[PDB]
Image (cartoon, rainbow, N blue to C red; front, side, top):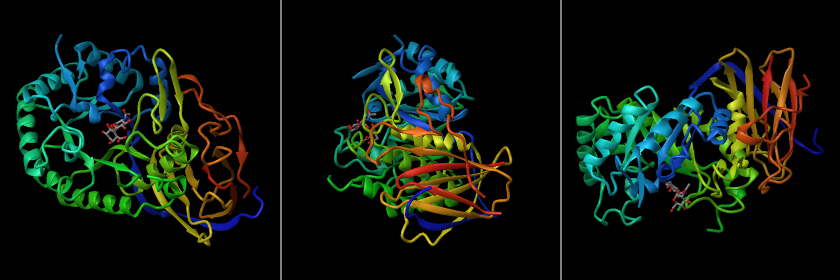
Length: 435
Ligand SMILES: *[C@@H]1[C@H](O)[C@@H](O)[C@H](O[C@H]2O[C@H](CO)[C@@H](O)[C@H](O)[C@H]2NC(C)=O)[C@@H](C(=O)O)[C@H]1O
């Protein structure tokens, strides 16, 4: 219980049907440069394989990023070898995840892309390979040196066509996604119109940071009107072209994250909330960007030093433990003095109702009167840290994540209740499960 909480109502409507969350919704995004060491994405990397399994029995590993500008496949600047691709196959087998694989359109040749694609299709195979992507954020190639100032959608469409044609010559069944950029009208909308028969889905990026002492934990917990616009833009592309969308690179802040924001418990609330907000908008899935010890990485570490779950991971863990199923109406009322509380109701594939709550209010505890659920018993797992800016001390279900993504709940809490009352501290999260 909490001292002076904001008393809010949550009404679940099992008749207000939303989108069905696919089982491969979860995912991660990594740099292609990781493939320069064949021990990274390897059957031997049992620690990293463990972290991914805990995030989902199904999910998508996306490899790409700015380093796909300067990674170069060779059958014998970073170099990708057949051994790296062979090892990646074994990693996907250990995790059960599917692959989005970046090809080098920024600096590589169409012929080298077709050769790399052929080797990936030879070894990873059609079942595990979801899509190739032809360049990462082509709209920023100029910013990053890789094309001249005059490079525009028309030029990129020419490149894309040349690469597509060369690859399909070597790999007739090759699947593609694109354009692998932030939402925008000059690139993503015309990409969808022009290449709708040649791609499986639209690939777009999102950073809560816009174009700075102004990305703060306070700002990160607030609604992002730009995100709502971009998501609406993607749904209109889907209506116009039939192409579903996946958020294939996202994190709290770009340029590697912001110390004191991206590496904090607040990122767990942000990331868990984002996963549900995009799933409710009809996104097919998500891929949080990371690697190394970057401020925003979900999993930190290396094969030689070992891996650990960073705060953001715990947001993704809450989503993982909720599991898949159909989103339901979950209306909040009396909530104007706790406006950053979000709630998502889910009919699980196993038939049980779940509710994911993110109390993103930094200074208000809440007391949630839950109606519209008929159950003899509800339990809560809490997503907690002692302060919103904590870089550690994060737990879920009263336990940290251990080595190799090991996680089990250690604290059982019943929700008192044809209604239920749930207290939540300021800056906390909760997963409710009803028998
Ligand atoms: C998405 C890009 O694809 C991604 O590569 C960016 O991250 C990398 O590059 C930026 C800019 O140089 C670095 O600051 C990051 O540390 C890099 N991340 C990793 C994991 O190596 C990414 C971003 O800006 O953070 C997006 O632009």
